[PDB]
Length: 419
Ligand SMILES: Cc1cc2nc3c(=O)[nH]c(=O)nc-3n(C[C@H](O)[C@H](O)[C@H](O)COP(=O)(O)OP(=O)(O)OC[C@H]3O[C@@H](n4cnc5c(N)ncnc54)[C@H](O)[C@@H]3O)c2cc1C
Ligand SMILES: Cc1cc2nc3c(=O)[nH]c(=O)nc-3n(C[C@H](O)[C@H](O)[C@H](O)COP(=O)(O)O)c2cc1C
Ligand SMILES: [Cl-]
Image (cartoon, rainbow, N blue to C red; front, side):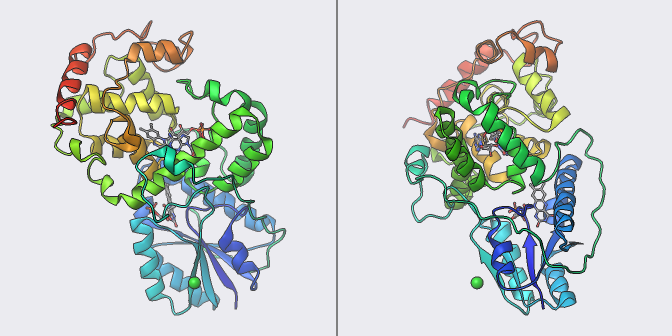
């Protein structure tokens, strides 16, 4: 009987510990389960996942191999596939998330054959004994990527079952699949890496790799990416790998501090008097704040499903600090709009930008939204693409008074954080 390789957020054949572990023991059949716990989300994100499952199937077929795709609860469908295939055992990459642990425990209960979970490739794993709140001490544990595992060359024949629905994303998707991902990585490392340190804070995000949507679904291994960048080397190289490490730091943080999905990491801010306000929330959410940078950022996000780091930190902080909007609502709304939307990473970014205790970033740093545009969109080209409404970064009729908002936040904040 075959071994089942169950792909979850790891829609690739390269650097895939579970796939090779299984192949070394016998013939394999792969499986994806379309799980409503993950797929009951926005069309853009469902489609991005589905189209990558479709690409993974194409990759299996091109190698002569068989990828099943079933729809439903994993603890019903994984056992179903095991029974139908007469599988000897199921292999998958460990998941340390509360849902991943819940689901995998339930699957192990329902399976009458072993479930073998292998460590997912990381630069640093999320479940180290020690709990860092600060990126620098965490980052020093990393000493360069281990080598990635090869993809299989050809795959053993097996039966294929199951359909992959076609859904409307509502917008243009990147090219799905690991072949497009690896091409994009190779091009970034050639063209852009040298100036990455100098260009990564552009509001247009064009100094970066734009590989997040692949990372978020495991279509590209972070180990492979760090490994390739380190073989390329140069100055941008250390700095770009540092950013891959912020991804791992985000998993580390949600792992050691799970409660941060409920409340600020900094207990000093847990009683901050946020102001619910529907009209205000909608103005932010729809990019109608009258603040050029924020409005351009939120309008690109709706239209495209992507935003540069520098745009994200400005859009997110603005809601929290200038508008005082409850962070949980905004956080979630923001994730639902992102192709690369990744709960742990988005939470990290929000708690960092909002000054809620990640990396002990200080409350007093408040983005001046006009300086930020002047400094990170030099000739206004990015503003002109995304809200040509506005002839400069000067607020035209802002939903709040901006200097008062700044004064009010800092007052409030410098007043919880002391005492
Ligand atoms: C409020 C906020 C919310 C965010 N939400 C998400 C999210 O849901 N999903 C997501 O993938 N990223 C999120 N980011 C992190 C980061 O902005 C994006 O990963 C980045 O813009 C991706 O662009 P890139 O692929 O060109 O990155 P590059 O600059 O080329 O970096 C390479 C890779 O490193 C990782 N990375 C880069 N910056 C960060 C960072 N600040 N934190 C963690 N990992 C990083 C990503 O995997 C990225 O693709 C968020 C950031 C903020 C400030
Ligand atoms: C938009 C999106 C859709 C996803 N859909 C699935 C899916 O249907 N099946 C699955 O096994 N993994 C899916 N994943 C990867 C999972 O999130 C993965 O199961 C992970 O190991 C545990 O889920 P979690 O992120 O909620 O903790 C999806 C990821 C994202 C970002
Ligand atoms: Cl085991």
